[PDB]
Image (cartoon, coloured by chain):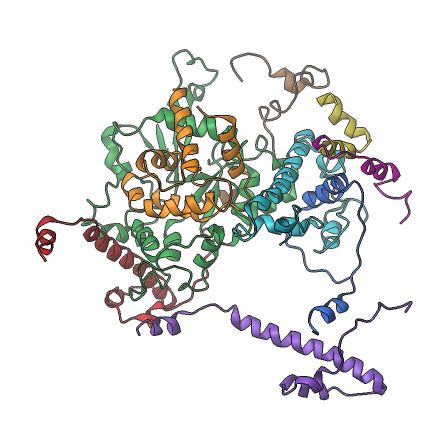
Chain colours: A brown, B cyan, C orange, D yellow, E green, F blue, G red, H purple
Amino acid sequence: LFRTFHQYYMGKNVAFVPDVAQKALVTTEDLLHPTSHRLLRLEVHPFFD
Amino acid sequence: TYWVNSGKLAFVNSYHMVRFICTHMGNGSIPKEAHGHYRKILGELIALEQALLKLAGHETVGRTPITHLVSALLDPHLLPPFAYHDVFTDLMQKSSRQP
Amino acid sequence: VIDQLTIDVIQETAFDPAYPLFCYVIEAMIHGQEEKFVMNMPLIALVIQTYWVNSGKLAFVNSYHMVRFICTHMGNGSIPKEAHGHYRKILGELIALE
Amino acid sequence: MAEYEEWHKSPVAAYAASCQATPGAISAMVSMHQKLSAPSFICQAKHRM
Amino acid sequence: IIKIGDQNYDNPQNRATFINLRGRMEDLVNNLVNIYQTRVNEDHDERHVLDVAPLDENDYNPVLEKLFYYVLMPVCSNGHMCGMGVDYQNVALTLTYNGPVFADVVNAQDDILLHLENGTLKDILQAGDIRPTVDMIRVLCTSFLTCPFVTQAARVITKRDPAQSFATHEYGKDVAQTVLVNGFGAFAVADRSREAAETMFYPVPFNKLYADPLVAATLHPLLANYVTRLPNQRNAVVFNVPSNL
Amino acid sequence: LDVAPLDENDYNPVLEKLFYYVLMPVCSNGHMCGMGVDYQNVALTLTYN
Amino acid sequence: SNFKVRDPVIQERLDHDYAHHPLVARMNTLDQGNMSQAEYLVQKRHYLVFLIAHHYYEAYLRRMGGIQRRDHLQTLRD
Amino acid sequence: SNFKVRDPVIQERLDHDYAHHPLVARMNTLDQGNMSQAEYLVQKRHYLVFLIAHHYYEAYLRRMGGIQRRDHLQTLRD
């Protein structure tokens, strides 16, 4: 587990954020404002993701 | 000698003296009464930059993040006004702007 | 069972800049074992006591098995009586939750 | 010094002279260093500052 | 399904080929040279066999462990927790190769640092400010015998609850979890002794409550380079975890 | 300009900035100055006796 | 160093400095094999770690046997 | 005194009062040059500051070498 750790962070210069990790930081009023299609588009079902 | 005679604690002045009394010296060399007040400083001063990362977005603009722009506390072109380790060659390598 | 005063102790250890590295060496050598802890109970009663007297915080908070073994297997006055009370309140909480 | 050329003008020093010792004045100085730019205002209008 | 690396683990009848147990130390005083022969010969990057102690159903209960790591520690530490991995044979090389441990001329009930040399134990015991006796470290040396190998991770793929077995795709009926075997989670390591932690420990981010960059940057100076190159990932919610964990 | 070299792990830029600009002018109520030192006069006092 | 941890700074050659010890005679009985001269010094040091631990645990079990009746009650007569 | 700090009040001529010291022989090896008689007493005093500091730091590094194995474990035999 020192190999799989060191293969991944060696020359990483770009960091990706999923759809889920950028919803839990948005407040309750920013998500409904119409400048955000993309977070609000996949808010389809209550129970699923 | 200074925490026992008067009720006050020395070495508040520079940051590097306040940092070294916390990181080093877990001893009983300086009193536990005066050891807590130095630890409350760095324990809070780290707890400020946690709040400064909650406001600043996870997203960027180009190569430069948004966190570098929104507050001058996070903007690295502001420098601490006393320099002991060589800041200037670090700042020229990372600035999109002209230093 | 947990009051706000004992969370105030557990949180101060988590933000400690001078937390001892030696209690990671012990916990790696115990690695959650019944027999291997009883061999070392005259050692961990020194790491806890020299970390509760030198500073107001308490050690061996990382894993569950070190917190469980301190509450059950001593029943004595090795750890100071104030410092041993904070460990009992942790397992008093977890049982009351379930 | 040229006081018209820094990120710290005069009225920052005028506020620190009459601060209280209260921990609210610590968070006043931290919320003071917002940058008055255009993409700062996006970061406050989301969080309702 | 337990995935120990490549090979799946399905049945309890195939327990001996995948899981190797190690019982009491007092019972294993006979087969104990056969343990050290497997420390040198075997390839631990492709061993695919995990070492755990045998468990007694009247001793433990999983709910108190689950109420501890998932409820009480993410609250009280506010999520500053990373999965610390241990290299075990490099730990006891500091302890046993001391010199006051090895030489039997030194008194057993005597202070350690009066006799100890410029190594890592002079710097690790200067962190904890501990004055143990020579009996104390010599008992810690004995724990090297049944000591396990490198910390491993096993991904426990189970099916979902019968109220939740409706899924878009075929993998969507299976929920999963990686359990770090023989490792332990740990707080922010002291910055006065990061040199000693750099010779013993390494970070393994494997879970959402246990992948924290401000803790993981202390354990290895390459992730301290990663956090300071791009400060987007200084949060726990945002931080990138490897696709193999 | 005689300055010791920078350790990347121990440089820590933001925390020096929170101490000098925020936490010190509150607690001192803005009573601070920059101090100059004549370093070869510091040895002649400490050593030469 | 992408595959292992950093090596600790410890003073070399404990064999020349003390012994006068029976377990160092057990160290020389380890065969060299196909390992080089520098690699033989490494794995001989690791084998010393096993011998010290097996010695002090064997000494520990005799210590925790506890005090027994017949030897103790005979000495209370004097 | 518009260009320097005030001079401290310290008793003069440490050379005549103690030595009996090897580093004062190093002081006389400093050449006078074009400096006057009063100015030679000044810069010879400043050179004594450098010799005391270089001596006690060289003595300090030997002190922090720590206790070593072979010399100590031999004396534990007695």
Please give the name of the residue rendered at 58% of the width and 46% of the height, measured from the top-left corner.
Answer: B35
Q: Position of residue D9 (x, y in %)?
A: 87, 40
Quadrant, the N terminus of chain E: top left
User: Would residue E74 appear left or right of B90 to someone viewing this image?
Assistant: left
Q: Position of residue E190 (x, y in %)?
A: 53, 47
Q: Which residues are magenta?
A: D1-24
- Of residues F5 and H40, the one drawn nearer to the viewer in this rendering: H40
Asked whether A19 falls inside the magenta stretch, the response is no
Q: Is residue G35 above or below residue E223?
A: below
- Of residues E196 and E21, the one drawn nearer to the viewer in this rendering: E196
Q: Could one spot residue A9 in this view of the protein?
A: no
Give the total of numbered labels: 0
Snapshot quadrant of residue B64: top right
Asked whether D23 falls inside the magenta stretch, the response is yes
User: Would residue C72 appear left or right of E120 to someone viewing this image?
Assistant: left
Q: Could one spot residue E37 in this view of the protein?
A: yes
Q: Is residue B64 above or below residue A46?
A: below
- Of residues D2 and B26, the one drawn nearer to the viewer in this rendering: B26
Snapshot quadrant of residue E163: top left
Q: Position of residue E161 (x, y in %)?
A: 39, 15
Q: Position of residue G66 (x, y in %)?
A: 18, 48
- Of residues C48 and B72, the one drawn nearer to the viewer in this rendering: C48
Snapshot quadrant of residue F30: top right
